[PDB]
Length: 215
Ligand SMILES: Nc1ncnc2c1ncn2[C@@H]1O[C@H](CSCC[C@H](N)C(=O)O)[C@@H](O)[C@H]1O
Ligand SMILES: O=c1ccn(O)c2ccccc12
Ligand code: NA
Ligand code: NA
Ligand code: NA
Image (cartoon, rainbow, N blue to C red; front, top):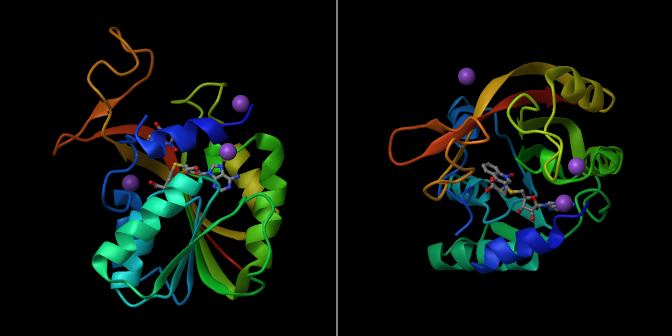
């Protein structure tokens, strides 16, 4: 019912498959299209490869994660790179304040399914409160067709639309790939999940890419 210990352990190295050392490809694709604007919030940032990429491009970025190990790793990576633009804080995405009207772009790179269904309303009210007028919002989340009921709260397209449309104006929801480097034999033989083998030793699982804004 709570993943806090699991995420803390995965970041402490007791490396996470989703820590691919680059922003998620579906989200990098939006960055090159010029969709990321002004001050950015990387919500449930983890090791924050997307925050680092945006800070290198000139954005002032803030990454929030419930995991103190994730925050420390994100801060350690920004310091190795000599980034002054990127900051990180330990926070619960479902219930945080102190950033009223701050951000022009809010990105959720796989945080969405990493919290309980019941926490979604608190999370959506928190990020809207943290949004500047006319802010953009991007979500990359697992598809319920690929990830079953259990520790991960993956969504159907209709479920994602219903949840987010209450708070933001949705521009697009389209199928997407979530990339990771899984260990050999991950999820068994035969495999209990549909894991696609990708070029450059990567794997991917089915998901959704949502694009929204305030207007
Ligand atoms: N309630 C919550 N508040 C903030 N972060 C949370 C959270 N629940 C889960 N998380 C974080 O959500 C992340 C999901 S994993 C994805 C991490 C990163 N965005 C990436 O793309 O690599 C983890 O870092 C986890 O600690
Ligand atoms: O194994 C995973 C557990 C949680 N998250 O969010 C992921 C994201 C992308 C790829 C893999 C994972
Ligand atoms: Na969580
Ligand atoms: Na669950
Ligand atoms: Na696509």
